Image (cartoon, rainbow, N blue to C red; front, side, top):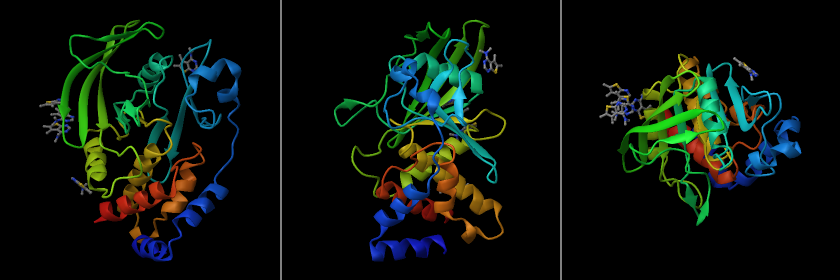
Length: 279
Ligand SMILES: Cc1sc2ncnc(N(C)C)c2c1C
Ligand SMILES: Cc1sc2ncnc(N(C)C)c2c1C
Ligand SMILES: Cc1sc2ncnc(N(C)C)c2c1C
Ligand SMILES: Cc1sc2ncnc(N(C)C)c2c1C
Ligand SMILES: Cc1sc2ncnc(N(C)C)c2c1C
């Protein structure tokens, strides 16, 4: 169909759960044997969320190359993303090692450190200019350079130093701070504004390594971000924008990481965002 009329037809027929279940039944199943090795148990936040072996990011290490992170490579749209879990106390040094080694320019964070009264990820960046962080396991230093706090998001300028080579790189931290503890936003307007601030920065462009995107598990909000970005780019590239099929794009992305879009409400929100962004 076309998207906006497919949308009203699923709303009127109340069939979001059935459409979402169809996607779950058709999604790819690839092995994740490295994720399940006993030596990696304290590197995974959730036992049911693992990177596939074929698409996992490898750390440049001989002892243990494992991180819970996946490369999503979208061939027609010419976009790549790394989707990862919120870092754990034992994996903050691995996280910044990955940003360094993959030549990323941007980190996109879609969660708060505490939500629903529980910790959803480690405090993995410095909160004050004069109190830098040193990750001794991976030999990196991270400094807060500047902060811009807005109503719906915060952007930070960070300096990452490889202490082995004394090389430095600027990293941009894009923090969406207002996703609700339960459900999805009522309007996609602030999420779309945020997506276009990340684009404007150069963080999604081919002159850099892939953007690093995370939430708590790195599949639900994180999936919504990459799915909306890729669908809007395809609508600009093709002769017939109404040919873009959001369900087919999501199944392509599910070849590279399991579980992207965690609820029927996140699926409806992704349709809403693409429909409103197209205008
Ligand atoms: C430039 C690259 S790619 C790569 N893949 C696996 N291991 C590596 N190590 C640990 C040396 C590397 C390096 C140094
Ligand atoms: C006024 C300026 S110049 C500049 N250059 C790089 N990053 C910045 N951010 C987002 C902290 C800024 C700000 C806020
Ligand atoms: C002069 C420059 S460079 C640059 N890079 C990323 N974002 C920007 N804006 C609009 C927030 C800018 C501006 C205003
Ligand atoms: C020179 C740059 S890079 C960058 N990235 C995100 N936000 C920014 N602004 C406008 C606060 C900037 C600026 C001013
Ligand atoms: C949904 C939004 S907000 C925004 N701000 C600046 N430029 C934009 N375009 C057209 C590239 C947009 C879009 C498409």
